[PDB]
Amino acid sequence: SGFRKMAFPSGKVEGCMVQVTCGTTTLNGLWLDDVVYCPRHVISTSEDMLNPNYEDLLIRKSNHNFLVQAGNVQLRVIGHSMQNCVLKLKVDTANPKTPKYKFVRIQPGQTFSVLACYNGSPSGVYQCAMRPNFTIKGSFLNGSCGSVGFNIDYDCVSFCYMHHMELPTGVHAGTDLEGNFYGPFVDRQTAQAAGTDTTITVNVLAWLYAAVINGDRWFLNRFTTTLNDFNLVAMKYNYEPLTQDHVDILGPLSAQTGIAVLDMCASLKELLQNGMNGRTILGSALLEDEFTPFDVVRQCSGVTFQ
Amino acid sequence: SGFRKMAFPSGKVEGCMVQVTCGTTTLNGLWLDDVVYCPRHVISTSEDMLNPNYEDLLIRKSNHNFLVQAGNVQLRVIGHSMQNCVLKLKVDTANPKTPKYKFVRIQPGQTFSVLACYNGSPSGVYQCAMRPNFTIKGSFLNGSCGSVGFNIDYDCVSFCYMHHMELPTGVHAGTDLEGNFYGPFVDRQTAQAAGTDTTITVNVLAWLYAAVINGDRWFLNRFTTTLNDFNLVAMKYNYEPLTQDHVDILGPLSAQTGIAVLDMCASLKELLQNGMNGRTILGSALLEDEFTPFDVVRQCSGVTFQ
């Protein structure tokens, strides 16, 4: 029983974390088969231009200008490349602890586990979600650049995020490991807007189903309605519109305890006009929106990763 | 920048998790140098859970009885003993993944990270705390016994918990690695409700400081309160008594933020009677008591002006 905010076991990712230094800038890097992946802004943030020119900053650099350190033993760089935001340092030594991995880009509403690293040493692991404004509300300090977010599929660390910079709002932005930034962001230091953040309704519905799996119903009432009878309600309460594809993926959770996904929406509506404040909703008062339907199944079924 | 419920990297613990099977019961085990630590009750039988005589059952079992698997490879047991609640299984193969470790018994209110495992493979990692009633609020399904809780100090895993049972109220009970339960619990079939969960005051005070170092200062403290009269209101609100030792550990956060320990106590009273009315302390509407002062300093490492 119980329901916590779980994160994936980070063991397979801890063995890939190295330290990348170019000049005086030092951040983290991901050591896959024989390539080290790190944000490209390790090559130009020592002279503090506020607008680095990464196209010409890399041509001058040679292989010996970089310094990849795998904890203790130094790594030889035998080639460098840049894929639109990230630096690929070709290394001579293949990482023996490379797991099965794949690069995948996530959509807003998806969740992943972040491994905060400093100087190549992992410090903590936490689970977060990709907000609709293409930002993440994580916990990063200076020197955490290069930290990655990931999921696991039976052995397969699907990397989906790499931390690049922090927005003035306090939220954090980054790219996928192909390089493309999540949202309209640039790796330069110019001030950029965070965007409009909306609570994820599809994750809220899944979270409410997790309460009735371990068992706390406490709100199921008031005249089950249809899809469009809740989209306009979400507009007023800052929540995002609910699509039918969200209902489609809410099937298994509805096909376990509840009657229909439509029934869950009606009870959620009263949770907006009214507040609990006397009995927590299985973890707290405020509604949590960082639990995808796929995360609830994983935690309630005890899925492991070998 | 940012504050989240992070857990320690579970990489070093995953390398110590094995699967222990005793005839018909299967749970997890902690594979240290040449001893596999798993909860006793693995040798017990469903028909004999009324009042198991573990000493009598341990004699009936031999080394060939215990089936220890480190993934796909079997470990041969060459001895079996019992530290009154755990089953030390002497094995022939020394674990090469053993990190520097030590068995520590934590006090109520201290936090640790839990690596939930099933059939010897990890499922997820999350952060929780030992509640004052000597129970934890975790997420465990059947077969999670043997999952351990731990902390890391820069090179060393401090094992402090091993999961044994789930109480009927939804909370979980376990032992230290030396085989001693936290609280009035035994591995039998008696009721064991464990009673009256209490809120941790030293942790919530630290959590209130975390909001200060992240852009939340609207819980202004006007007056102050001494050590005793603070406990006058902390007995009816069901809060852990605050001691001068708790003030000493809160010293570094008091100096870093400039708010005195006694001053912050008076700030809590405004949030109690008046409620929220839309007030969210940086992460939720309710108070969080699973952040020790050490966790706050660890995560948002500020500076102290003196």
Image: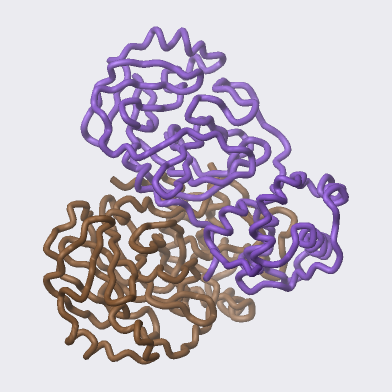
Chain colours: A brown, B purple
Residue sitting at x 55%, y 72%? A199
Where residue A111 sits, quadrant-wise, is: bottom left
Q: Is residue A223 visible?
A: no
Rendered location of residue B34, percent (x, y): 31, 26
Residue sitting at x 54%, y 80%? A169
Q: Is residue A6 visible?
A: yes
Q: Look at the image and tell me in which quarter the C terminus of chain B lies.
A: bottom right
Residue sitting at x 31%, y 41%? B15
- Image side of residue B208 versus residue B262, left or right: left
Rendered location of residue B225, percent (x, y): 85, 57
Q: Nearer the viewer, residue A40 or A179?
A: A40
- Image side of residue A124 versus residue B93, left or right: right
Q: Nearer the viewer, residue A301 or B159?
A: B159
Is A254 drawn above or below residue B39 in the view shown? below
Residue sitting at x 83%, y 50%? B227
Rendered location of residue A254, percent (x, y): 49, 56
Is B254 drawn above or below residue B153 in the view shown? below
Count of all numbered marks drawn on residues in the image: 0
Is B102 drawn above or below residue A61 in the view shown? above
Q: Nearer the viewer, residue A165 or B192?
A: A165
- Image side of residue B101 versus residue B252, left or right: left
- Image side of residue B76 versus residue B109, left or right: left
Is B275 drawn above or below residue A9 in the view shown? below
Where residue A129 sits, quadrant-wise, is: bottom left
Rendered location of residue B81, percent (x, y): 40, 16
